[PDB]
C-alpha cells in the first residue's frame, strides 16, 4: 500500500506558500513537481561526474556515456520495449511527434493519402500532421467526440480506407481524462496497413504501459510530466520501422562519415536521430525519476489516484451549477466550468486561495469548440495530492459561486 | 585582475580524482564544467519555484514565465542584440543551425543557388547545409584552408556570385582555435545580398561578443560550453529576418489558433519557433551561467586564458616530435599529434595520468582530411585551468614519447 504523507515528504515544493497561504498544487497535468531524488541526482552528476558524452577516451566522458545508455535501457524496460535501441531521446513529446512527422511521414505519406487523428488531441498531436498534410498534399481526418468525452468509435469504417497511412491518437486526454481503447484501435489500423503513433504524455505516470502489448508503432511521452526534469522526453519506434527512417536533424554524432566531395553517410538508429550534444543532465534526472516511480509501484499509484478521484467527484456534487466535462472513469484531471463565470476568473480566485489549477484551452482548441466553450478549468489529482486539497478546492468553488453569483 | 584559485573553488568537479590521481580537465571545448552558482540555481528553482510556463494564471506558473523571459533579456544583452525578441531558445548550437537551415533555408535557397561554408567547420555547420542543398538542388561551396589553419581569403571572389544566398562560418574553430575575420567577411557577403550565419559555439566563453558590431544575420551557441547546463542554447536572428521566417516545429505555444476545419495560424516570433514545453530548468541555469561569467568579466577571462596559452605553447616546445595544428594566436584549444603515435594512444596514456583531453576527429572530418591525418589530440585551456595542469600535460607527452618511441 501507499503512504501519501511519505511521498509528499520527498517533494520540497509542496511545503511552499503562495500568496501567504499553503500551496495546493493541482496542475501536474501541465507539469509535475519533482522529488529530491530527481533534483539531487542531476545536481550530483554536475557536481562530481560531468563530461561530454560522445564515447570520449577519458574516464569522465566514458563513464558519462555509459550512464546515458543505462538510462536508455531503463526507459526501454519501463515501457517494455523489446530493445533499448528502439528508444530515441527527444526534447519532449512535441519534438518526438515532429520527428516522426518529418522523418517517417515525408517518405510514407504521399499526395492523395489520409491520416487520422481524434478531436480530443493535444495541439502537439495535430499541428505536425496539419503541416505534413500541407507538405505532401494528403488529407487529415478526425474521429469525432461523444458528449461524455469518449470517441465515436462507430465512425471508424468511414475514416479508414486503403489510403490511410497513419492513426495518431492520444492514450489519455490531458483535458477529459478519457483513456482510449488503444489495443483494439491498433488492431483495426493494422488491418489496413496503417501505422499508429500513440501520444502517451498523460499515461505513463498513472499506470503501467506496455508497448509490446499495445503493438503501437510509435509511442511518445515527456520527462517533466513524469516527475522528472524539463527538456527531455522519449520516442519509442518499432525497430523495423526505425531502421528504415532517414535522419531529421543533421550534425555531429549522427554521421558515420562527413566528406565535402563524397557527401555524408549516417550512423545506425537510435543515434542517427540524436544530433549534437544531448541533454545529459536531463537524461540523468529522467533515469532517477523512473527509479523513483518504479519504487513506489505504478499499481500503488494507480490505486491511490483512483480513490482520490472518486473522492473528489463525490465531493464536487455539492458545488452548485458546476459543469464537468468527460467520462466518469476519468484518469488524472477534472475539467469543469462554474456556472456562467469565465474560467479565467474562477482560476484567479482559486489562485488567490493558494490553489493552482490551469485555465484556458489546454492546447486543445478543437476540444473546446466541440463543447462550445472558449475555456475550461482543469484540476490535476496526482499521486502527491490529498483529500484536504480536494476539500479546499470544493470550498473554494462554493465561495466563488456565492460571491460572484 | 583574476584569481584562478578563487574561480576553481566554485567548480566542485575540479577536486575529483580520476584513476586514483587528481583530475586535470583539459576538455572544456567539448563541454565545460559548471560552477555551484549554476548547479544550485537550477536545483533551487526545482526545489521552490517549479511550474509549467505558458503564462499560467496561478502564481508559480506566472512567476516561472517571467524568470524565463528575464533570461531571454539577459542573454540578448550578453551578446548585445537590439531586442530580447531576437533570441530563440534551442537545444544547442546544432538545433539552432538546423532550425535556420529548414525555416529560412527552405524559402530562400532555390535550385541553382549556392551556399558557402569553410573547410574548418564543425559537422553541425556542414550537414544541415548538405541536407538543404539536397532538398532544393543548390550547391555547397567551401573556403579552403591555409597550412597555418587560417582561411584562404583570396578564394572568396571565385566563390561569391549573385546566386550566393548564405555564408555559414565559424567564429572560432573548435580544433584549431583560429578566430575568423567575421566583420570583414560579413561586409563582403552583404555586398552580394547574402546572409551570414555565424557558429559562435567556441567564441562566447573567451571574449565579449557583439552581434550588432558584427552585423551577422544569425548567431548560435550552446549553454553547456558556456559553463552552463546541458540541453539549452541560443539562436539569435535579426528581427526583420525572424519576423518573416515560417515555423519549423509545430505544436502548442507556437500557435495563435488551431482549427480542424479552418486550419491553424501562428503566433509572433520568437515564440513561433519554440514548440512545446521549453527546457525551463536549463533556461534558469543558463541565466545563472551568464551572470557568473559577467561577474568575472570576459576581458579578465580573455587576459588570463591568453597568458595560460602563451605559457603552454612555450612549454610545449620542449616536447620532442610534437606536431601542432593551427595559428600561433589560437584561442582556447591546442590541437596536436605526438610523433608517429596514434592520437587514441596518446589520449589513453594521458587519461591514465588523470589528464582528460579529447582525441578523434572532433566532429571535423574535412579538417582532419586537409591535414592528412585521421585524428588529433586537443587540449582545452579554459579559465579554470592552471600552469601546473599545463606542466602535467608537458611531462606526460614526454614520458609517452620516451616509453613508446
Ligand atoms: C564550433 C562548434 N559548433 C557546434 C558545436 C556543437 O554544438 P552542440 O553539440 O552543443 O549542439 C560545437 C560543440 C562547436 O564547438
Ligand atoms: C497529451 C499531451 N500531448 C502532448 C503534450 C506536450 O508535451 P511537451 O510539452 O512536454 O512537449 C502534453 C503536455 C500532453 O498532455
Image: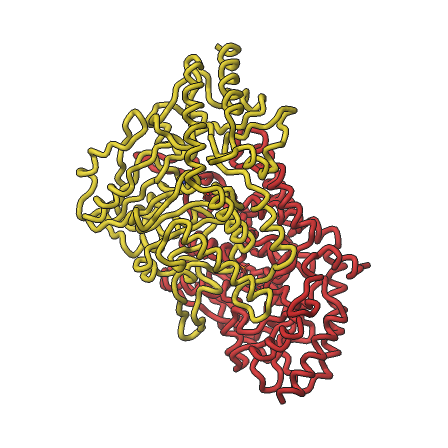
Chain colours: A yellow, B red
- Which quadrant, please, contains the C terminus of chain B? bottom right
**Direction from residue B405 to residue A250 in the image, left or right:** left
Of residues A9 and A263, the one nearer the viewer is A9
Ligand 2 quadrant? top left
Of residues B350 and B220, the one nearer the viewer is B350
**Direction from residue A92 to residue B34 in the image, left or right:** right
- Which quadrant of the figure has residue A304? top left
Where is A118 relative to A216, above or below? above
Instruction: List x then y, in percent, for residue B232.
Output: 56, 51
Q: Is residue B132 visible?
A: no
- Which quadrant of the figure has residue B324? bottom right
Which residue does the image show at 76% across and 74% down from the upper left?
A: B311
Where is A9 relative to B382, above or below? above
Of residues A305 and B49, the one nearer the viewer is A305
Instruction: List x then y, in percent, for residue B174.
Output: 59, 67
Which residue does the image show at 57% across and 62% down from the upper left?
A: A52
Of residues B396 and B190, the one nearer the viewer is B396
Which residue does the image show at 49% across and 71% down from the upper left?
A: B142
Where is B372 relative to B143, above or below? below
Q: Is residue A318 visible?
A: yes
Where is B393 relative to B136, above or below? below
Which residue does the image show at 49% across and 17% down from the upper left?
A: A397
Q: How many marks?
A: 0
Instruction: List x then y, in percent, for residue A276.
Output: 50, 60
Amino acid at each position: 500500500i501507499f503512504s501519501v504523507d511519505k511521498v509528499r515528504a520527498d517533494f520540497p515544493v509542496l511545503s511552499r506558500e503562495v500568496n501567504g497561504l499553503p500551496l495546493a498544487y493541482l496542475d501536474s497535468a501541465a507539469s509535475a513537481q519533482k522529488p529530491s531524488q530527481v533534483i539531487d541526482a542531476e545536481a550530483e552528476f554536475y557536481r562530481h561526474g560531468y563530461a561530454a558524452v560522445h564515447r570520449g577516451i577519458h574516464t569522465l566522458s566514458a563513464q558519462a556515456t555509459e550512464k546515458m545508455e543505462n538510462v536508455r535501457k531503463r526507459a526501454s524496460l519501463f515501457i517494455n520495449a523489446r530493445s533499448a535501441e528502439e528508444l530515441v531521446f527527444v526534447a519532449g513529446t512535441t519534438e518526438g511527434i515532429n520527428l516522426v512527422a518529418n522523418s517517417w511521414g515525408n517518405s510514407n505519406v504521399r499526395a492523395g493519402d489520409n491520416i487520422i487523428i481524434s478531436q480530443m488531441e493535444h495541439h502537439a498531436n495535430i499541428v505536425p500532421w496539419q503541416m505534413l498534410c500541407a507538405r505532401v498534399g494528403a488529407e487529415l481526418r478526425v474521429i469525432p467526440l461523444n458528449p461524455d468525452g469518449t470517441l465515436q468509435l462507430e465512425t471508424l469504417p468511414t475514416l479508414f480506407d486503403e489510403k490511410t497511412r497513419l492513426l495518431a491518437i492520444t492514450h489519455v486526454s490531458n483535458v477529459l481524462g478519457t483513456e482510449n481503447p488503444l489495443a483494439e484501435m491498433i488492431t483495426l489500423a493494422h488491418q489496413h496497413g496503417a501505422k499508429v503513433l500513440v501520444d502517451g504524455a498523460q499515461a505513463v505516470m498513472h499506470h503501467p504501459v506496455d508497448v509490446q502489448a499495445l503493438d503501437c508503432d510509435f509511442y511518445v511521452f515527456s520527462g517533466h510530466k513524469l516527475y522528472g526534469p524539463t527538456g527531455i522526453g522519449i520516442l519509442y519506434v518499432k525497430e523495423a520501422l526505425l531502421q528504415e527512417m532517414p535522419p531529421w536533424e543533421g550534425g555531429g554524432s549522427m554521421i558515420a562519415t562527413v566528406s565535402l566531395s563524397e557527401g555524408t553517410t549516417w550512423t545506425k538508429a537510435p543515434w542517427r536521430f540524436e544530433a549534437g550534444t544531448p541533454n545529459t543532465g536531463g537524461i540523468i534526472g529522467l533515469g532517477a525519476a523512473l527509479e523513483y516511480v518504479s519504487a513506489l509501484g505504478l499499481n500503488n499509484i494507480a490505486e491511490y489516484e483512483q480513490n482520490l478521484m472518486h473522492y473528489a467527484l463525490s465531493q464536487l456534487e455539492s458545488v452548485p451549477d458546476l459543469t464537468l466535462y468527460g467520462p466518469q472513469n476519468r484518469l488524472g484531471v477534472i475539467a469543469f466550468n462554474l456556472g456562467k463565470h469565465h474560467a479565467y476568473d474562477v482560476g484567479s480566485f482559486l489562485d488567490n486561495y493558494g490553489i493552482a489549477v490551469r485555465t484556458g484551452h489546454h492546447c486543445a482548441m478543437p476540444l473546446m469548440a466541440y463543447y462550445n466553450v472558449p475555456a475550461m478549468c482543469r484540476a490535476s489529482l496526482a499521486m502527491y495530492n490529498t483529500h484536504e486539497e480536494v476539500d479546499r478546492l470544493v470550498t473554494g468553488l462554493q465561495r466563488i459561486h456565492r460571491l460572484l453569483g
